[PDB]
Image: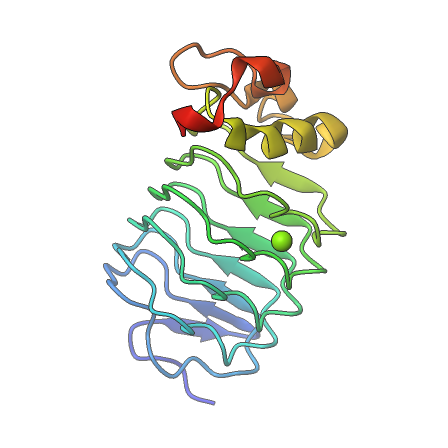
Length: 192
Ligand SMILES: [Mg+2]
């Protein structure tokens, strides 16, 4: 039940933000619900890093230096409602990474290096009310963009809700035109 040496704990919250950390601290108590890991220098999460924190409802890992996530890294976080991943350098997300987050209402992916989202990545996010996708270099010439294009069109009111610019603030790299307007004929699997 003890609070990790580098962090401070209050109620169900574990505060590990702004602590110059390179890794998630060991020994976070398993009953804690809100975990702040933002504003550190975490460059890589090890697989399974969060597996014991089955009560988490809030997880913020924004403003770190992550380029990828391990397969399954959120799979045990059944209660998660808010997931902050902004201000990293993710170049891709793993297939299936959000499949086990049925209570997730907020997903913050803005300010990264994402070029597309894998087909079906949001299939099981049946509670999602806010997703932030702006400030990513979306690759609109590659046909892999078509899942995201069709998903944001369908669910326009949940994408970048005010004041974050709406569905139109999901922009193609280079041309800076809206992802929602990409035509299938303008894409190709050979430019991926
Ligand atoms: Mg799938």
